[PDB]
Length: 330
Image (cartoon, rainbow, N blue to C red; front, top):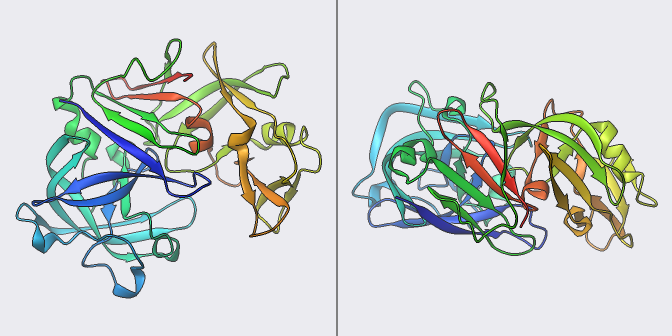
């Protein structure tokens, strides 16, 4: 089997991407944030505290003839941005772009933190990291990809995120029309439950490539590119007037600037992030200070190849017995 679904930016900055997902019988379609940095499929629901729902579409398990309470199971998750959610668990039929999994754990939110309530466009998350990170207790549950894998034509999914435009998540096949050149594959460590890999270095604009190993995660659920402070300083030093602002929470730059590109290495190959992809717009409405799309990971504990980086590439998440990642230009 295969599946193919369009993913759409939630706003004009590509802060996140939503993908329609069919849950239950008859189908209830919710727009989920596909997150290769986490491993829970959770949704706003009829069980979510009413004051914490503000415009989202909810899953109502009582209206699904295939929903079954997973007795005794609870979940609770906290994300790198400080947001969180928790609740109980159903199993139900879940389909993405024509690919169907029966018996998928659908984690129903009873509580969500303010940032989720405040984002009316995201109805939940669909985790695509390794199932060892799934938070369901006392019986850990498998991701949608893990459940579908054996049925797929090939044990892979691909992320093709757009810049200010829709893109595609494919399951079970590699669309050879969706990228240019060849796909360069690189080793993955699953020891932390992430799609963790080592970039071979970077360049800023037209500058020379610096060969240096940068361990990080391919994380579709993180907006920005978080890299070591040395690398980020070298990037922003090429932008007149850019500075790190403790009060804003990262590097800002004059909105009048033209940003240089940023290149990262994948083995001997190179992925170029155009400068425009690094502009996240005014820090507040009407400000001439703009927020940068490359930020320091120093306070995180891990480097994160988020959407800023991934949307410059066609990315293969290869879930073979030994997982690997593939990157192509597009």
